[PDB]
Length: 38
Image (tube, rainbow, N blue to C red; front, side, top):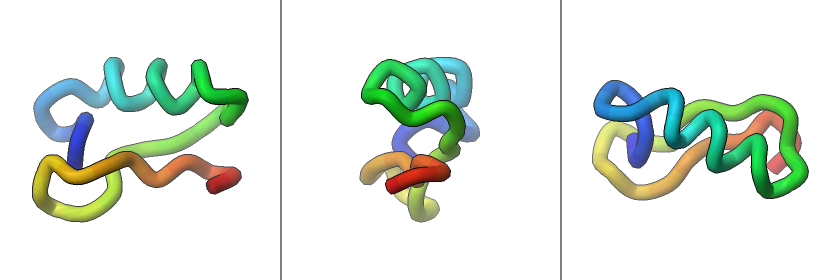
């Protein structure tokens, strides 16, 4: 995905910064991140 496996901390913190409290990278390619609450 966008963050993992490259930078999970970034994707994670990034998603966490948009209100979401959890989330990971969405898709295999560096597209976006899948937040736990969209």
